[PDB]
Every structure is written in C-alpha cells, then in structure tokens.
Amino acid sequence: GSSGSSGPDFTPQKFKEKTAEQLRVLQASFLNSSVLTDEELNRLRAQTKLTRREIDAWFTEKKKSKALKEEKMEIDESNAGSSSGPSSG
Image (cartoon, rainbow, N blue to C red; front, side, top):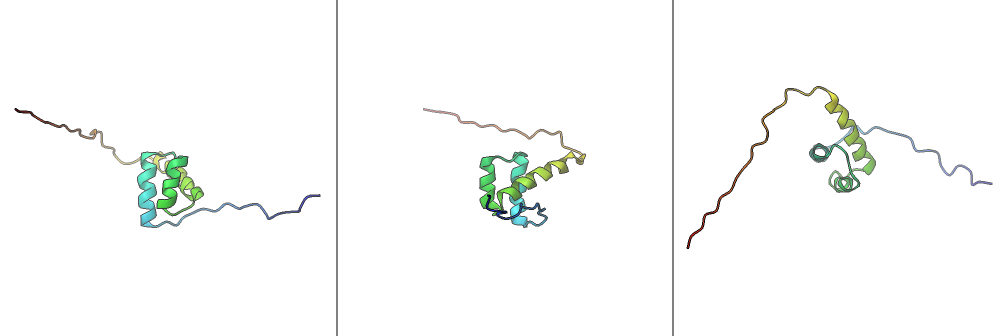
C-alpha cells in the first residue's frame, strides 16, 4: 500500500521575539506597503535574516494594530520644494 506516515503534520507557532535591527527594517517596510509581496518579501528575508513565513505573518498582525484609533493625526500635507537655474551669454 502506502509508505505509512512519512512524518506528522507541521504545527503552528507564534514569533514574539525580534531584534531592534530586524524590526527597524520590517517596520520601515510594512509601512510603505502594508501588504507584503513576493519581491519585498525576499529583500526583507535577507535584511531581517528571518523566514518568509515569519516576515509575512508579522506584516499581517501589524495591520490589526492600525485598526485601533491611532492618536491625533497631522493634516499638514508634506511640504513641497522647487528649483531654479538662470542663464547668460
């Protein structure tokens, strides 16, 4: 018939342990793109030196954090800039 079991089924597990270095990254990324992509995922996989599952899982939970009515926000829209460049002859 069939081999047999070939090992049990993988079990879930939370990841509540990160280093300021790793976080400083994930946080700096997740912000720009709340949703993780196959691309961004890789980059972080090397930066945070963590697993693809860990990173992704993190980005998710984070979202929830936002759900909470964050403190007063700043309406002041990011200021813009300009440039010049005269001529002569």
